[PDB]
Amino acid sequence: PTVCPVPLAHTPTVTKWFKGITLHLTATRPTLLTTRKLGLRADATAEWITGT
Amino acid sequence: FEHATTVPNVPGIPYKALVERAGYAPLNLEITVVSSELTPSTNKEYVTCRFHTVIPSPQVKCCGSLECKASSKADYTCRVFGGVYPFMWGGAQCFCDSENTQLSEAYVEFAPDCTIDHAVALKVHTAALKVGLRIVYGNTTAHLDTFVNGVTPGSSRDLKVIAGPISAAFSPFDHKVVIRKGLVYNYDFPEYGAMKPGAFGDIQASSLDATDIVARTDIRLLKPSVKNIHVPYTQAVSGYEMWKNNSGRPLQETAPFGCKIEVEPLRASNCAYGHIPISIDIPDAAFVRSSESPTILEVSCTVADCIYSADFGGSLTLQYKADREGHCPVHSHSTTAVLKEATTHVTAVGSITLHFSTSSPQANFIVSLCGKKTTCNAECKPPADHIIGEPHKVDQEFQAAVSKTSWNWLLALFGGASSLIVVGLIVLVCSSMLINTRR
Amino acid sequence: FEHATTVPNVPGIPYKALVERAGYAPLNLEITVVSSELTPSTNKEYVTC
Image (cartoon, rainbow over all chains, first blue to last red; front, side):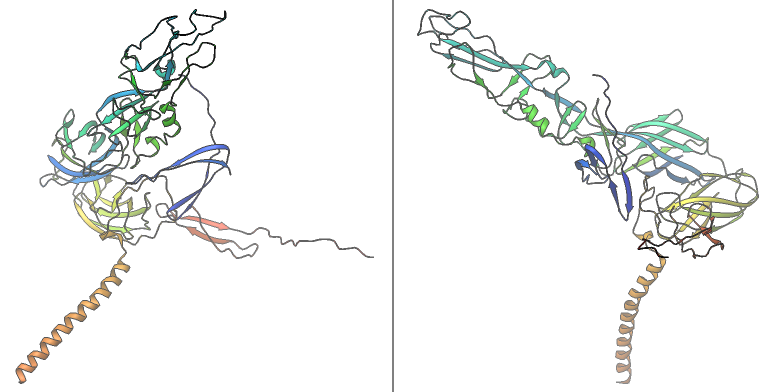
């Protein structure tokens, strides 16, 4: 084992609205986005995103 | 003195309470769940990884016969074939064109790189929740680690506390768990001994170095066809790789209640759910009797602009007239409002400005200063923002969650019908009595 | 903290407002249109003399 360097994606742009958010995302290569609720139901969603 | 309360199991959010001993002055008690650790008890059923299909060099009984022995290797497979007449490099290996049997032997072992690339299978049992807790009373702060079960007490050198049980037990881990390079998955792995080829746990062992490896990889040996020497075999793909491709996201990204999964040992830290009943024996030494503490004479409340949100978006002022300079503890006696400051310097006469956060549309709550209670009445507007990076510090109830305008309208509308039915009943009664009297 | 106002388009006359965040003291906002230019989309058709 050792330490490997990995890139950091462009910071998302978050737009708020009543009980919700909109993340504008830019990633030239496939970047993983994983969201989950902190309640009884996780409602976990995972997606590899490319482009903008 | 012993005090019982119910703290909300949410890390980082303070919970404030007031203990009101009859003889002594009221005292503050603030409580913060610094960290939690929901850890289960686990046993290692087996470990699995890529299998190295090792094929011993074939032997030929050059002009005789062979019989397959019964070894105890993992997925051992041995077969005997008839005359082959094999070639190595010199055009011949035997002298009998027929009755030149060959023995094809093959089995599996652990790959050389499984010491890092392997998955451990575990079963979980009832999980005990442990809490690191910071509690302050008056002047004294205390850190203590305790078990939330209702029997095991935590202690800090003068202060005894007992916590739990949790209101609703919960465990993010299913019965069967798989650990892979620290990643946690809830996979129903096959039981030990029940190998199936082409799926997870096709090769199993008690440990990496264990020699009693058992596997079922569907390896089969075929007749050698080409003239040159070799042992052909077809085998199902490694089920470890199949699970790796279709593993899915780990439990670190799917556990509910915002619980942070961790390994070595398996645990779930900072897991917010339920309420912890806590009974605490706060010492009487810290208590200060009312005869020495400043008991204020008359206090009044004037509320400024307020807003119901997670952040401290409410402000108010207490205009107080007291008799001595001291350190009164200020508190709120409502479940839908929480203050920022705990102990405030009180003068003979003056005013103190304080902050608070509420969940109700209105601030209709009682504030206490050195025991004296005053009802603050306000009207909080909806929050201007939409999202915060902070948690809501107060639960939203049903009673104190609707404005007095809506409450007044609803009560008027319902009382209209109630008044109507009662006036109808008395009208019927009076008509009957009038009929009876004038009959 | 986003505050929305309807400032009269009058140069030289300040417009004053008070922003009142709930948990914070009010703040004064003076908004003064120092200059304002309206330019149309122009294209030369020809010249003459």
